[PDB]
Amino acid sequence: TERKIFNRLKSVLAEKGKTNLWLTETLDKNKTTVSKWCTNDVQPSLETLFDIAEALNVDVRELIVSTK
Amino acid sequence: ERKIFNRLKSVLAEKGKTNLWLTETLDKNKTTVSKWCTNDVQPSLETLFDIAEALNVDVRELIVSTK
């Protein structure tokens, strides 16, 4: 696969009015870890995605790009 | 205390495919695929995308919905 884009965290954070700093603090994470999620450089684990979804109050499915 | 994160077993059943089919299609080990199906170990998000492509399903369907 040539796919580079797997998550849409950056978009969901924008929809919800939350910053990378907010997510970083809320989840007790390191700043670079969160940054690389948002740029699709490093993907969160599926368990982490559920934690993100809970923090943001969105269906976890919305954090992933559709392949329909 | 969530234990169930994926719907792989359910989607395989929907699509009429077996674990063995997935192991051969993706070149993975049986026990690895089994552990995904039983929600004992989760695949990476990238591997989830590979599984979705193999199954011709929206990757989102592989994950338990939280709303």
Image: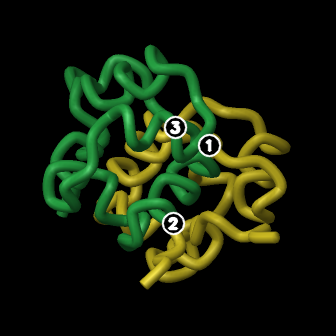
Chain colours: A green, B yellow
**The N terminus of chain A, quarter of image:** top left
As drawn, the label of residue B43 is 1
Q: What chain does badge 1 belong to?
A: B
Position of residue A51 in the picture relative to residue B65 (left or right): right
Q: Which tag is nearer the camera, tag 2 or tag 3?
A: 3
The amino acid type, in three-letter code, at marker 3 is Glu
For the point 68% across and 58% down, the residue is B19
Residue A38 at x, y percent in the picture: 29, 31
Q: Mark 3 highlights which residue?
A: A25
Q: Mark 2 highlights which residue?
A: A54
Q: Are marks 2 and 1 on the same chain?
A: no
Crowd rating for badge 3 (residues with CA inside 10 Å; few <14, some 14–19, many 20+)? few
Q: In the rendered view, would you say B64 is above or below A30? A: below
Quadrant of residue A57 within the rendered picture:
bottom left
**The C terminus of chain A, quarter of image:** bottom left
Crowd rating for badge 2 (residues with CA inside 10 Å; few <14, some 14–19, many 20+)? few
Position of residue B67 in the picture relative to residue B3 (left or right): left
For the residues bearing labels 1 and 3, Cβ distance under 8 angstroms:
no
